[PDB]
Length: 13
Image 1 (spheres, rainbow, N blue to C red):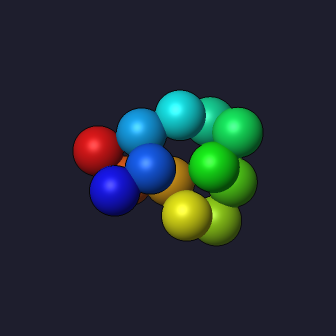
Image 2 (cartoon, one colour):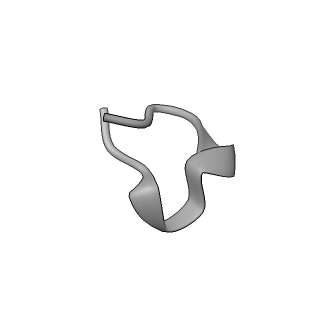
């Protein structure tokens, strides 16, 4: 997961 808008295309919560 990458639950932060800065994750960009990786965003997931």
